[PDB]
Amino acid sequence: ILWHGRVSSRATCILGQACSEFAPLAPFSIAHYSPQLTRKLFVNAPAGI
Amino acid sequence: STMIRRNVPTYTAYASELLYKRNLTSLFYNMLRLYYIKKWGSIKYEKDAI
Amino acid sequence: MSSLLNSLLPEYFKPKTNLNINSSRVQYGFNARIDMQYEDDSGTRKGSRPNAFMSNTVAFIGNYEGIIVDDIPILDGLRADIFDTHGDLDMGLVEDALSKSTMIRRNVPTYTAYASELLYKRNLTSLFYNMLRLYYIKKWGSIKYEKDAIFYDNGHACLLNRQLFPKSRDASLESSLSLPEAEIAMLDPGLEFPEEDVPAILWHGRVSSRATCILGQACSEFAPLAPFSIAHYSPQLTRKLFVNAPAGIEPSSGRYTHEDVKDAITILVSANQAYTDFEAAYLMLAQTLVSPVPRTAEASAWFINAGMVNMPTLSCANGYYPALTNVNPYHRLDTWKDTLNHWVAYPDMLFYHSVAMIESCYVELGNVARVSDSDAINKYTFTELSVQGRPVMNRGIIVDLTLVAMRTGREISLPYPVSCGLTRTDALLQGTEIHVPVVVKDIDMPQYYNAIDKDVIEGQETVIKVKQLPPAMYPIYTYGINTTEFYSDHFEDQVQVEMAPIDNGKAVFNDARKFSKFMSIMRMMGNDVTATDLVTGRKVSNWADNSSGRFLYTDVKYEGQTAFLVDMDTVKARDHCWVSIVDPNGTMNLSYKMTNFRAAMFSRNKPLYMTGGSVRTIATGNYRDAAERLRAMDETLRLKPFKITEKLDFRVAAYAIP
Amino acid sequence: STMIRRNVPTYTAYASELLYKRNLTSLFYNMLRLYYIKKWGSIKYEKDAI
């Protein structure tokens, strides 16, 4: 994916959790079961992650 | 463009497959769910409820 | 802006280039001929003072403190190709411009990504400001500051330099600062990724041995000993400074003269194409070069707490992108080089431009402090309605330029809405009591001044409670151009005090307006009048100043009901060249006329004369007509002959032109 | 109205959530009550009055 300038300290944590398995305990509608989207995600940002 | 000259021939060959991989719907879907989980995070679910 | 500050100067004032300042106090003013008249039922008594000196004392001392703030970027200088129709950096033409240049091919993709952040870091105002201060420190370096010296004295109350400025050691201006040098590294053109939070500047040819020492000291902390105006406290601008000079940077010399600082500025502005940045730095220093000595003892409330100077953060990314600066720059106004060209020609003219600006501001803040909060244009909301732009915050130069616009009564226009410099309106907006310290001389002080103690032995340190701020300066350069009835700065004026013979000299002024004009004109005539308020029971004296020689109504030091008893058999003749009121009977009519004006300056109780060449009004056209001319005389050495002519003697020879 | 343009995406996100809840009416209400408590601060309330 592409990015504008520098990937912030919090943007790493959000993208990391977005591309992961949802394994819920309580049956909630916005926290349903989803498979692992991807294992690794590249980011073309000249300013380091 | 501003590409490395030794990569142009090898990257152009791959273009036929890779340029038709454009669907970010799954990523935006999960990121929208994380927004509402942290906003309305204080809602409760009881096991023995009606 | 040299243009707008030039128009503030009077018509009769014809300035010269050089001004040999050799002290930390100057009495600028004018000599006028006053034809006073006193008419009465008995008869008329005429007087005439041929040389009457009206002065405003201006010093080189004043407590200030610099703070680094975030300000808008100044986009004047960059090439006109990369800009779009609206006037903002169209990114896409930047990538096109960098590609078709003399850049390393492996750096193009990584440098273009950074462009979005780095190209909007253009503000060199902080660097030019410090380099201008170094010029004047080395020029007027021999001025002295004594610790136990008289800041103000009016006979009754005295205020020393120890009182206002503690932590203050006596020293010369040259010996005040001990500036440490910042590192001036050479930029490697083959650097992988640009280092943000480190500014990189351009240079023409080789950085000289003295240029290193000047740039090193300009980007450093100012930690002064003596409270000087051009050597106030400033934070460290930057730690390291890159310079993209293919010819290597020579090591620091250590010493430099004031002429070498002018050399450093002229190269920096030309290479970087930063003329609007210099114009901002020129107006900043114009505010904070000289501070006014207070007119009255209770007018020291303005200079108790230190006014903050807003210096914009040093940020420049020209060193990383040499291609984007060329000989065809983008500029808003056509007269964008006028401010630099004026300074290079006439450096010492800044002194006259400085006093013109502070005199304009402190006069208007005098008659702004005397308006009630319940009004449309009041103390808090006089800046907002006047400003028709989009500045970040209404502070610094915006508040000082809007006060000048009110004084002259004209429209002031700047190319960029920059908000940097000193903020004066600090003590005003607080709207609280200020406690100024004073050392007493006489024992009958606290009747006149609103003192904290009622009985005080001589040589005691007391406190005066100032509620409403009196005017700090009287209008002198702006005399009778935009006249108000408060100051009463007319050429012709008259007052009619109505008394009957049944009254034995005693007159009660029910009106406040004509009481002010009576007490003022009596002081021109050299008469010491002492009125007493009937309601409160305090006393006021017209002799409350030794500079202007006028009586403003704020010298009463109290707002209440107006019932001033003046006894006209206790009037004492004080000054020379005076008309006598021996014994008046019936209606009195006082009047004066100011006819001609001659510019005069005093320093160390001696006349200070202007020397050098005749200063002109430099226009953009006056230089570029010589560029239109080009000296188009083909540079061909054409030698013309002289025919010898013989006459009677023949021993001696005589040459003719044809 | 800034030189540091790295913070614009973050600033916009927080501003959008806060601007729709701005109200200083409750602060001025208490500040006005403090003015009149000090001014008329000699009024007596007797419990066994009519």
Image (spheres, coloured by chain):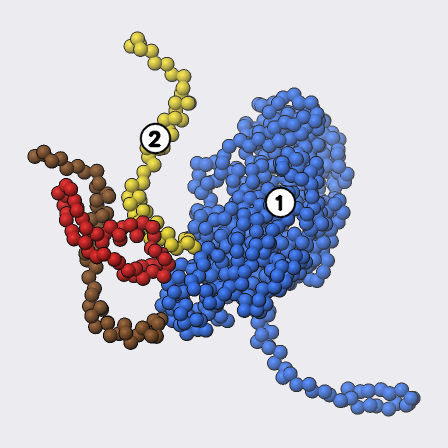
Chain colours: A red, B brown, C blue, D yellow
The amino acid pointed to by label 2 is Tyr
Q: Position of residue C37 (x, y in %)?
A: 71, 40
Residue at 90% from the left image edge and 90% from the top image edge: C650
Query: Is C415 on the left or on the right of C112, as rendered?
Result: right
Examine the rendering and report whether any part of residue C336 can be seen. no
The amino acid pointed to by label 1 is Pro
Quadrant in the rendering for residue C348: bottom right
Question: Relative to the observer, which residue lies in front, D38 or C576?
Answer: D38
Secondary structure of the residue carrying tag 2 is helix
Please report, as a chain letter, where disc 2 is located.
D
Q: Position of residue A36 (x, y in %)?
A: 19, 54
Residue at 65% from the left image edge and 27% from the top image edge: C461
Query: Is C162 on the left or on the right of D25, as rendered?
Result: right
Question: Relative to the observer, which residue lies in front, C324 or A18?
Answer: A18
- Badge 1 vs badge 2, beta-carbon distance below 8 Å: no
Q: Kindly report which numbered mark, 1 or 2, lies closer to the viewer in this rendering.
A: 1
Secondary structure of the residue carrying tag 1 is loop
Looking at the image, how many numbered discs can be counted on the residues? 2
Examine the rendering and report whether any part of residue C166 can be seen. yes
Badge 2, how many Cα within 10 Å: few under 14, some, many 20+?
few
Residue at 22% from the left image edge and 54% from the top image edge: A19
User: Which residue is denoted by mark 2 in the rendering?
Assistant: D29
CA gap between label 1 and label 2 equals 47 Å
Question: Relative to the observer, which residue lies in front, C256 or D2?
Answer: C256
Please report, as a chain letter, where disc 1 is located.
C
User: Which residue is denoted by mark 1 in the rendering?
Assistant: C224
Residue at 45% from the left image edge and 59% from the top image edge: C195
Give the answer, above or below, for where C72 lies relative to C107: above
Q: Position of residue C430 (x, y in %)?
A: 49, 36
| Residue found at the very far top of the displayed protein | D48
Where the N terminus of chain C falls, by quadrant?
A: bottom right
Where the C terminus of chain C falls, by quadrant?
A: bottom right
